Amino acid sequence: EAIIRIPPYHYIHVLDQNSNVSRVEVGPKTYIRQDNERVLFAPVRMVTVPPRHYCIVANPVSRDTQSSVLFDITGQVRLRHADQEIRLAQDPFPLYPGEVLEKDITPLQVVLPNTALHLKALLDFEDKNGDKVMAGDEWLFEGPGTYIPQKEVEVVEIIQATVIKQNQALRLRARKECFDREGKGRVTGEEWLVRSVGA
Amino acid sequence: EAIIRIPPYHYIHVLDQNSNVSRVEVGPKTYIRQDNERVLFAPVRMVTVPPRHYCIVANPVSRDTQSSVLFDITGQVRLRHADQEIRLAQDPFPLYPGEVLEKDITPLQVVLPNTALHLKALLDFEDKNGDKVMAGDEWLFEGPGTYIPQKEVEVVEIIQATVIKQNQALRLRARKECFDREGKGRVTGEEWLVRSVGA
Image 1 (tube, rainbow over the protein chains, first blue to last red):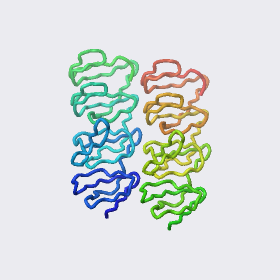
Image 2: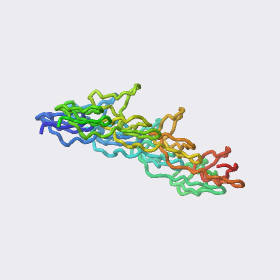
Image 3: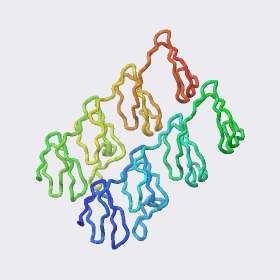
Image 4: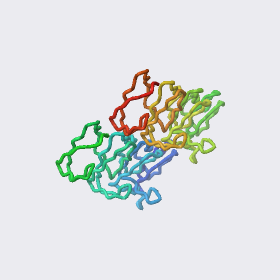
C-alpha cells in the first residue's frame, strides 16, 4: 500500500528510488508515500534514553555547531561513519538511515565509595580539562559518583581498594617506571609497602 | 460502532487518524467518535490515589508553571518521556496517551520510631532545603513519620537501631572515610565503640 501509519512516537526509513537517497520519517502523522518512495520497515519506537542511563550509536549524523542534522547534498543524512556519539539522557529521538545502534538504555556506571575504574584510551583525545591522552594511557577513576561512558575512553576493570588495618602494610609491585605514594623511583618488578592505615 | 459510553469516572484514548495524534477523553459523557476518530480501549477507571498513599507514572505530561496539560503543536500530549511524576494523593485523574503506570495506590512509607531508611540518589538533584546530592550520596532518614517517595531518591534498606543497654557498648566499623559520633577520623575498616546508653 501507499498509506503508512506512524503513531505519536515511532519512526521509519524511506528509500526514495527517484531521489536515490533516504531520510528519517518522524511522526506524529499517518503519512502517505509517493510512487517513488518505498518504506523499508514498520514503525519502530524512537531511541529512548531514561535519566541516569545512556546509549551510544555509531555512524552518528554529523551536526554543525548549531546541532542540526545536516542532510547531505545528495539528500542522504551526513554521517561520520567511523565515529560515535555519547547520548546521555534525552527524549525519544529517531535514528537516521545509516546508524547502527550499539549501546541502548544501558544503566550508567555507578562507582562505589571504596572502588575505582581502570581506564584505557582507545585513541588520542583532549581530556575534560585539556590533557593529551595517548592510545594506552592508564587513567584511574575513584569515586564515589557516576562516570559518563565515553567513545575515546574504555573501562578495563574494577579496582577493589584493599583495606590496610592497624599495624599492617600492603606489599605492592610496579609494572612500569611509575611513582608510588612517596616519590621513590619504582622500577619494573620492584616491591614496597604502604604506611598509613586507610583504605 | 461510532457511539461510546464513558461513565462519570472513566477515560479512554482516541487516535484521530486524520489528525494523526491522540488525546485524553475524560467524562462524564456518552461521547460519539467521528469518522476519523477510533477508540483504542474501553472505559478504564481514572488513576485514583487515596489519602496517605501514592503513585508515580513515568513519561509524565510536562506542564508549565500554571500546571496545564500542554498539548503539543502536533496535537499529542507533551510528555517528558524519561522523567517521572510524584503523585501524592489527589482525585481520580485520567492518564494521557503515552504514560506508563509504574506505581499505583501503593501505601506510603511508614518509618517506625526506632528505625530508619537507607537512601541512595539515582541521579543528581537539588534537595528539599537546597543541597546538591551526588549519584550515590548515602542519606539516612530516621523518623518516626512518613517519607514521601521521590524520583531522584531511592530507599535501599531498613536500618534497625541497635539498643545498647546499661554497661554495654556497640562495636562499629567504617566502610569509608566517614565521621562517627565524636569527631574521630574513622578510616575504612577501622573499629570503635558507642558510649551512651540509648537506642
